[PDB]
Image (cartoon, rainbow, N blue to C red):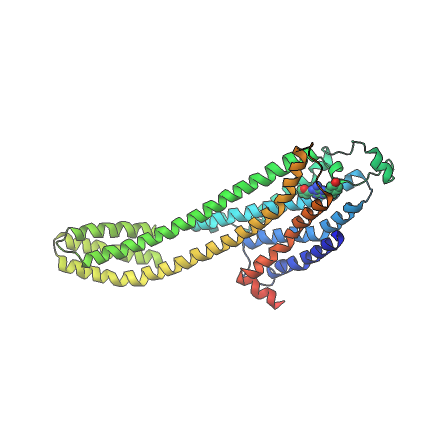
Length: 375
Ligand SMILES: Nc1nc(NCCc2ccc(O)cc2)nc2nc(-c3ccco3)nn12
């Protein structure tokens, strides 16, 4: 039962995520910093699928060996999880930068810096993974009955997770800080990302609404005064929207508005409306082209952000229950120990996470869809 599902999930991990690594290599279209991060995460998934499943299946029954080796068997999954969480945080930061500040996105994001951050986060993940090895372990604590049952020699120690790895260390430091604080920061980042996109779309629509309504009032107006009032709002909206296509269009538009305002200050309303009709051409052409490009660009950014948010949510909801039951067991010693059959089920769910990643990229991103069908 348990042995069957672990092997079944393991096989889907390699072949499922090797395509994601394969796709980034045989498709120049899908190659950027976000893909570099997600392929680092995919390499972490490859590593967990290849190694942790045999490690879990051999530690589930028992494999007596040196205490350091057994501790490594248990910390390898944790380091491959910390790598994934760091990669997800980097992805979230990349998306926030790209959407909030598109002008400086290319300036502040570079491939060399992305590779450097990937290396830094991987070695940092190794730091947490190897932290229990050095000094913080439970090797010194005797288990007489156990070591007699498995026939443990002096050098070799039996493998039993909860009694070989520091439970208090795990529950206190491993969960709280380096899981949650990344998760809370990531949630705040995603909320900020969506708020920024909504605000930007609202601002563009408001500027278009002003540049249309004021013009309509211009033809539907009279006795100057209102004309000079409306062109002031036109200038304000045009400058705000501007802050070769966009620049030249807005320069021509503000020049025409200045001409109309200068010609209407003298009191010549007929040619004031003539100049408004003159505006009506540049408005249509350049402003409509700019708006149609901007809306599609923002929609694409929002779609990418939603995809990555879904990946994050799946990661969190797959790695949450195990830690929750672990901290429940730690903080209620008087409570009866959690059932073995349920604990194994939760571990299966956690490892399942690696399988889920390629399915999202094969179902939502059309760029990966074509190349997977190619294979
Ligand atoms: N609680 C736990 N158990 C095991 N394996 C030991 C299975 C077991 C659990 C309870 C029992 O009474 C006898 C055996 N691996 C485990 N890995 C983790 C883990 C990975 C990341 C965070 O926690 N927790 N965890």
